[PDB]
Every structure is written in C-alpha cells, then in structure tokens.
Length: 104
Length: 104
Image (cartoon, rainbow over all chains, first blue to last red; front, side, top):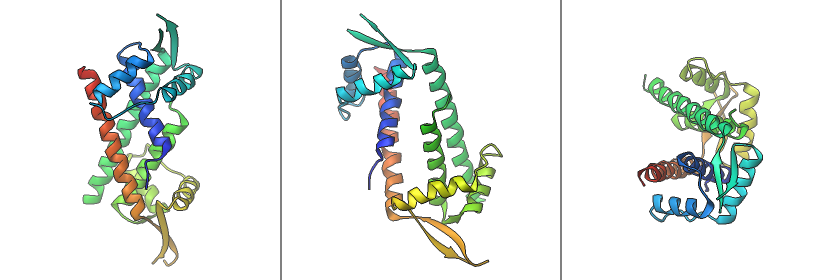
C-alpha cells in the first residue's frame, strides 16, 4: 500500500546523519553526495533538508557554523547514532532468533 | 538517548515479523518475543493491543477467533505483506546508498 512517512523520515534522517558523521557539510554538498552515492536515485528536496536540520539543531544533535552554512555532528549526535545502531543490531538478532526458534 | 519514535519503529518491526512467521495471539507473541530476546524484551499486553488497534485500523493486520475457544488470533493481511516487502526494499536501498557514500 505504501511506505509510511514516518519511515521515509527515518530513512532520510539515517542517511543525513551518516553523511554528517563522515564530515561537517553544507546542504548542496550533501544533496550532491547523496545523489552520487545513490547513483541518481534519490533527489532530496532542499526544503526537506533544511527542515530536518532545523529539528536536529533544536534537539542539539547537530550544530551549525559559517564557512556557506556548514553543519556538524554534536556529541549527543555521535552517541545517539551509536545507540541507534546498537539497538537495531539487537533487534536484527531478536529476529534471527525468532527464525531459528520457528525452525526448531 | 534512544528517541521514542525509534523505539516505536523497532517494536512495530518485531511484531510484524512475528506475524509474518505465523498468525499468532497476544500472549503467544509476548512469549515468543521474550524467548527471542533472551529475556531482554518483555512486552506488555496493553502495549500490543495499542499497536494492534492502529495496525488493524490501517488494514495491515486483521483478527479472527481460534480454538480454549475465543482466542483472538491476528494475521498479516495482503497489504501488510506488501508493506513489509516495500520496507525491506527501501531500507536495503538505503544501506547500499550509505556504503556508496563512504566509497566516494
């Protein structure tokens, strides 16, 4: 039927945060990086990126500075990405276990 | 911290995979999830009813009576299987996008 918007938001947030984890960056450079990495699939909407960056700065997961407006990942952002990845690997294991128990 | 949005998404993912393995009932789902999580993730009945009412409302699952007699079993609808498929697809696309971001 659809990919829920919450899940679209989550995918876009995940991608953007990994971009910033590689390095402080600015919007156009991120859109280029993601279009290139996506080999052209994903045209991010600049207004969408500005919106998400605004929410993240509000939540102190990223911060901004001038160079062109650059955005870098704060400590809260680094630790929260670590917790996200760890949590999700735990989830993937739970599901691997559900499969094994189903077979047994 | 782990955002509440991310907790919700993970719990949804686990539940839908439980049902993908087979039609099941609330208490049986909670037992299976406790077993797969080796005791970490012990879900609350009221939580499952909250999530199942929304999922049923959105036509991703349906319910019917089984057996004891009058056990409420829940099944994954055709739409639910499709949404799980599109989700798994889009998320694998994203993970590839990100390997590519690094490669560059």
